[PDB]
Amino acid sequence: AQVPLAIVSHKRQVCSLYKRALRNLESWYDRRNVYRYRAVQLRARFDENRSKDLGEGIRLLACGQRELFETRHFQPRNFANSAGGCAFEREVIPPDWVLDYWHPLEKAQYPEYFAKREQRKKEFVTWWEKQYGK
Amino acid sequence: MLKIIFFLLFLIPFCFINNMYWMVQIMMFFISFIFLLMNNFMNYWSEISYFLGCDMLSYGLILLSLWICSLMLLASEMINKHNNYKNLFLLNIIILLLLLILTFSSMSLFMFYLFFESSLIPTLFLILGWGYQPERLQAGLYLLFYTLLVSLPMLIGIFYLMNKIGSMNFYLMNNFMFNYDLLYFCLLCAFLVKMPMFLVHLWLPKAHVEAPVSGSMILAGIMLKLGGYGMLRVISFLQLMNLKYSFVWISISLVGGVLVSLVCLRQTDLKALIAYSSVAHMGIVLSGLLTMTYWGLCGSYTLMIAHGLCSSGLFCLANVSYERLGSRSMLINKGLLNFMPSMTLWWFLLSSANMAAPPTLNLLGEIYLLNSIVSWSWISMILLSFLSFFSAAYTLYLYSFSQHGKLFSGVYSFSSGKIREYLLMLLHWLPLNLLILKSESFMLWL
Amino acid sequence: EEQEFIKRKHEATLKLRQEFLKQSSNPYRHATGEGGTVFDAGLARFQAMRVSNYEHFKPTGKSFRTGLFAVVLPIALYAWALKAERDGREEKYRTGQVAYKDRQFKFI
Amino acid sequence: GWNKDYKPGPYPQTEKERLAAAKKYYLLPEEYKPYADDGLGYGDYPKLGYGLGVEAKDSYYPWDYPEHKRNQHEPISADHDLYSEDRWSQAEPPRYSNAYYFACFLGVMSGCLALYYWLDDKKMYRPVAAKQYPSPGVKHYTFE
Amino acid sequence: MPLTSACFNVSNLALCGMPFLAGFYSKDMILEIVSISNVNMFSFFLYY
Amino acid sequence: MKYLSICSISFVNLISMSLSCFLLSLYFLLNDMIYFIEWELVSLNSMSI
Amino acid sequence: PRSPMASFAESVLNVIDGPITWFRESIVEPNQQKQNWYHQRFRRVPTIDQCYTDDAVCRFEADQQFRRDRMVDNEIVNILRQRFEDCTLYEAPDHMVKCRPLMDQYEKATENWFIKYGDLGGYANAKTAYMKQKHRLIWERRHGPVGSGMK
Amino acid sequence: PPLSLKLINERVLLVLKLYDKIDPSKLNVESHFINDLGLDSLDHVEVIMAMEDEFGFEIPDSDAEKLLKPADIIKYVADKEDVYE
Amino acid sequence: LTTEDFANPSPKNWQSYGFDYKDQVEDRKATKSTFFVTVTLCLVWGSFYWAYLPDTQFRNWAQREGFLELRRRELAGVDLVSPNYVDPASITLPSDEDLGDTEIII
Amino acid sequence: GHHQMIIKPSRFQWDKFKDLLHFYVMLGVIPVTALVLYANIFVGPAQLAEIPEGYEPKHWEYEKHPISRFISRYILNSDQQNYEKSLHYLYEENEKA
Amino acid sequence: MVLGLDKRALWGALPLLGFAIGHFLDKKETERMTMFRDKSALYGRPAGSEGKAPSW
Amino acid sequence: GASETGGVKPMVIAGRMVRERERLIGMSPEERAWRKQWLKDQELHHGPRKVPALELELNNPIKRFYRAPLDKVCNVLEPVLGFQRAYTVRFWTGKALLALTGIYAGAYYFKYNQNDWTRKGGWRVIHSRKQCVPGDEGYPKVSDRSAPSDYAARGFNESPL
Amino acid sequence: TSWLGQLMLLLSGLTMFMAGLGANFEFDLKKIIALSTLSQLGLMMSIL
Amino acid sequence: IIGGSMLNWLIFPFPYMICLPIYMKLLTLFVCIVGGLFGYLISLSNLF
């Protein structure tokens, strides 16, 4: 696994700007018939000035950003089952060792699970030994 | 009361005999049961043994002392796990128990002061012999010398009283009244440090933080109350002088209350929250007490008792975390609802009692104290409202953040809830619900 | 982008990510079952500073003005107001202006 | 180690101490910036965070402890609370400034309140007669 | 959902005061009691 | 709460209790009674908690 | 029994009263021993006025008499309150019918109770109460009715 | 209901066949955005944005740049929803 | 361990009740003894003893007279609540010269 | 039925705790319930009445209930006991002072 | 002496011995008590009702 | 010896992949093996096996008895309506008996042990008078609370002395 | 019978109208319902 | 659905008598209806 660097290119500062704009259309226009109209009307506004000098790009951000911030829906279409959702992250689960501390009679309900649980545990130990040669 | 005293002395040998931690424990509870049976008192001094009496004010205080002193042994078992001189621990506890009984029953002021300040030692053993933090040293310095630096000076006031009075039985002082303007400060302030007062709260957070579960339970459960019990007995003759100079004390207590509550919000340690919280509640107790009105005093007696109980239970909770996750911090401790949900019930309940949710002998207090203060001065209401408001505020934060958020990633497998701790939490709370049925014994003492 | 400030932090700071994983997944000290947590410097730093900053406290004009207006003036003003109002009310009471009919809180 | 072992040092007063302290807190030499140490300062403790809010920090970044959006060894801000998502903090810049929020509320409240009291002076009604009550000595007259 | 849709109708109409449902029995009787009793301009206009 | 859903357990006693309350409400209406049962705890300075 | 449900509520009233009153007559009367319990009559005491300057036992006796008397008079205020309480509950229209005729007893009781015991606070014994009366008598004789300032 | 890996594949395929500005025939499932699809700087995020709305979650802003193929999109959806199995 | 080990655990191990981690019976007898002494002995019998305690503070007796004393004063025609600790005639006020402005209190 | 497990801490200790609580409390309650039912139904309440002028109740006469009768006479020192206690003790202390 | 109370109640007697000694001592205090035994000013019987009735 | 697990090996298996974000950003083929294995043995088919004496251990003798008079019904009534309906009949017989029993107890206690002028601190009761109706016995009814002594009677207007 | 009536009629009237407006613009279904609750409750407190 | 009816027939022994102007009693219906007009009109919007 790789954790990305935080450096950003003006292309990304401009394209993710287009992304947020599309979102801001949603939060201000809902009807998909209405939307695709205005979303493609937005595209022309991102297309008429497609390629400009860097300096103009900086002023273009100086206007673009304000438009989002000054025209942001007071209730953005925050996404349901993602971070910031209206019901996301409803519950959590603890690390498996909690299952390790079941009372032996508590253990005695799912022997097949616990047996396989025991096997996988030793095989994980081998895996972790590998993970950096211990 | 010599019945109790001789019982405790004949319990002392069990400390030497090996493997008597649990035998001692049952006996201490059993004698508490016996002391429960002995109950017929009125306002007058009763059960007048050679120099030991007992009364409404002393009877409940003793019961709490015997109660909490037995609950120590439930709280602390790591001493047995470690074999960390269990004999010295048990001997220290019993010695402390005897001193408390003799302090609360000393019918003489001087006998009272004698045992009162004799308790300086065994408590210091309890922190130092079983402390954890390196701060344990400087903490012991704070505890002992804040106390002695004012607790010694009342020794002059006591003897001055003798010379002008001829004795030190409590009824005898009540017959007289003194207004020399130093007697007042010398006795008052000397008790105020152990109360403690917001301006001399300083030591108390340190003592609680770097002390074991047992010592902290003792410190917040009796020592603060013992200071107050002396006040109730002594202010009888300080009235006129108190009336002239009282606005200062009530002001700093009330002002300090909202402040220390805001300290609690910003604080980030379980014992620190409870320690500051206990100072806050004892701020209101000091206020109603210094009102000296009937409502204030009879309510103060109740709030001391209830506050001691709730503070103990919260300390057992703090011990539980400290003994599982090995760190007092708010940050490390979190989401315990996922690991001990049946325990988080008790977390909520003890928190509930500390924010004065009924049926709760604590709550019964604030009705009495708040009535007294409001009558005494309407101006108080502007700060009484905020004082209780922020009281509940930090308790909410303590309960939520500790038990609610998503778990901590780095946490090494620790055993789950167990009968000792479960029974310990019920035992501190359930009597705190019981008493309301018969508050009259815990509510009327004047 | 500073020319690799983000990168320069990147190299070292991503190393201890793996050591955190090694610690967390550590089958051995998790097997000991004694509780406790993987050490974390920020936590240890934070506790120590939280408990001790007096050795840093310099009693200057800032701290004095800060503390003065923090509690002192609050304590003094509130206490003075309380004493002043009580002095007036008690003055009426000892003058006997209000008889045993009008007065309130007859029962504390 | 224990807290006294970890006690932060005094504020660094020459560049070498700045290099040392930044390493003490794992910070880069510019990342490290001690407090003003003017009379109520922690000294060498770095001054981090204090931004608009913790939840402004990356939502999806790989976090060792997502709970506080925190990676491993890293100097916790002296005011971690008072900026935590559980406490005073937001995710995005506010739309307006403080006066706006208070003004928009309270200015309306004052005006509508005062205009009500003006209109209470003229309390309308249905033009009906006073409610009649039987009683000794009362002799309202029937329209007959 | 024709059941949930229909039920959500019943809640709307009870809350909307469509005649001889909950709102009509309650919202009505209040509003003319406002008329009967002498009241203030805003309080009157604001209810409606 | 070991063999039957807790929802069942509370539901049935709840419907049973409130129907009893409802019918008692009628009794109160047809007679216009107002009971004020009281159980005192303590009393000091002439007040009665 | 005009009304239907009231003609039914009676039926459950017969249901509820049935077993209990049967139980009272069935397993109480054949199982009860007769015994008597009386009510104190504490002798009067030489009050603080009587006792000497330093007669600690006598002073202690006086205070206990004062406390018990306080507890009763403390009470007589409560009973009058309970009595007024019933009247205000008597009938929905019936408030002014007997409020003042009945309450004013409670009003006088409060003021008298205040004068004797009020304004002393806890710890108050017979001495401070008794001398307060002395002070009030002096004030009444010198400055006139309390509630007039001074001359 | 659970989610089936094959159906995730056909579903991203359905939207891809649906999207006009892509090469209409939807050339090889592993069509890189800048190579044969020709997806411009902005057309790339239009792809991601539809995928979002279709699959009920935002893709992270930089992590879209990790998504450089319809195979990636399946691979990112699979990591989310436990689709390997 | 394997399937049958988990399915039917042996009677060797024992789950400590938090009191003693060495002997099964010592732990169980401690918990058994501790539970009895604490719960039944105080929180049943003791609660029972209080709940049936006799008049200790004489509150009930105080409200014995409360009915009588009030009733005694109401047919007696004397003040129900006399505002004098003793008879205002029994007291003997000293003369104004004795007073000499001894800060008389209301 | 199609059960998919859930990671849950142990409930055994908590369940045992409730069971011990229910067990011992009923243990104490049963003889207590027996005792209270006995006295009240086998004997019941002494009836209030006047003084017979020639009589003098002993302190146990002044409590209505029998369990009070048993407690006060046998277990608690009389108020008159704890009254003279003080009168003695205050006599010495006043004299000594 | 069921082996669940072995040596435990046996030592536990001594605390009960303390209560017995404590009881007897305080009862003797009730002996030095007697100065007003029936000679008070509130409960004090004037003369008669003795009848071998040393109230407390 | 002593333990809590009986000797189970206190570790955790999952690894980096516990976090939804972590699994979702990058995760190796060996990690795909474990995670699939983890979510593969997540399933369960048979059910919570029964431990006979576990119920006994968590059921004290005092509880055992009063289960019997109503549980003994189940063993015979179970086949008639099945276990689910049989227990349902058991339970509501138990609760119905409890409720009706308490009702008479409470009605008794308000009939014979009210808070009168002797005992105090109990449930003192007080009421208002019924609503007359034209055509009723003593329709134009007079006030019964003749004198203030009537108010706050608490049994004292019916004193034995 | 005192100015508390005037003060409450101010507030209850205002909030029901403030809620009666905010409900239109709010999009979180449960939130709109809650606003209707306040809008209705304000009426109750005003008639009272 | 039955709603207030059961209460309305069993709560008011003295139903409040309200004989108001027709332009007031009916006004409660149309000032009510214009809201629904706006609620279902302002929502219904043509694209451009």
Image: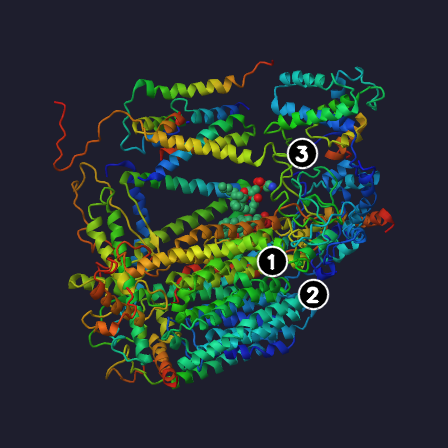
Which residue: 28% across, 41% down?
F32
Q: Amino acid at mark 3?
A: Ser
Left or right: G151 in relation to B430 = left
- The image position of residue E39, as x and y in percent, is 33, 29
Given the image, what chain letter belongs to the residue carrying mark 2? B
Q: Quadrant of the C terminus of chain M?
A: top left
Left or right: B345 in relation to I1 = left
Q: In the rendered image, which quarter is residue C81 located in? A: bottom left
Q: Label 1's element?
A: helix
Mark 3–mark 1 Cα distance, whole angstroms, equals 37 Å
State the residue lying farthest toward the right: A133
The residue wearing badge 2 is B134
Q: Nearer the viewer, mark 3 or mark 2?
A: 2
Q: Amino acid at mark 1?
A: Ala
Mark 2–mark 1 Cα distance, whole angstroms, equals 17 Å
